[PDB]
Image 1 (cartoon, rainbow, N blue to C red):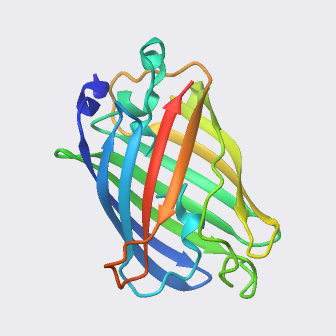
Image 2: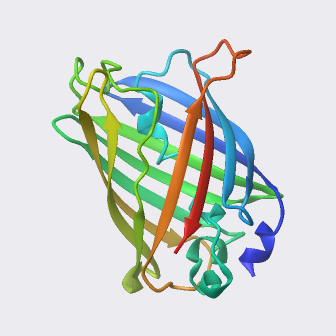
Image 3: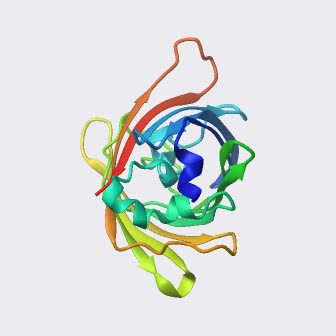
Length: 222
C-alpha cells in the first residue's frame, strides 16, 4: 500500500513559510525517517536570519506518517495509506493568554522524498509574551494525540494540549486543533480511534552558525 513506501529509510524535506505578528521567516529542514522504528532525525535552519519565535513552538507543525504502527494496527494508518499523493494537515494552535498559529501543510511524496510543505500565520501575539519574547526553555514535553476518524471529510481530526516550559518556571499552554484530509482520490483507510505517542529531543549542532534546531523523534501508535 502506501505503507510499502515506508519499509525503508526515507529522506525528509521540510519547508515552512511563516508570518508571526508581521515577522516573516522561513524554515527549511532535512533528515530522514524510518517508520519501522518510528524514528525521525531532522535539522531545521531558519534561512531568513534569527527565528522570531522559540523553536519548541514549531515542533508539532514541522509527519505522523512515520509512526511505528504495530502489525495488529497497520489497518488504521491513515497517514501512510494516503501516500504517495499525501494529505493536507491543518491546525490552529492557541497559545494561552497569547496569540495563535494557523497552519496548512501538504505532506506527500516528491519522488523518493517525503515532503512537508507548510504555511504558518501567527496573529495577536504579545510582543513581550512568552513566544515573541523568547521566554520558553529549549526542551520539550510531548503529549499523546488521540486520532479520531472524521467520516464526513474522509479524514481524521485531533485535539491535544502541549505544555511548553517557561524559563524560571511555569508552563505555556498550546491548545492544538487538527484535521487532515487526503489529497488523492484513492482508497484511504479511515482508522479506528487510537493514540500516537511521541518522544522528542531537541539539540544543537556545534558546527552550525545559523539559527537552528536538531530534532530527534520517536513515534508509535497504540
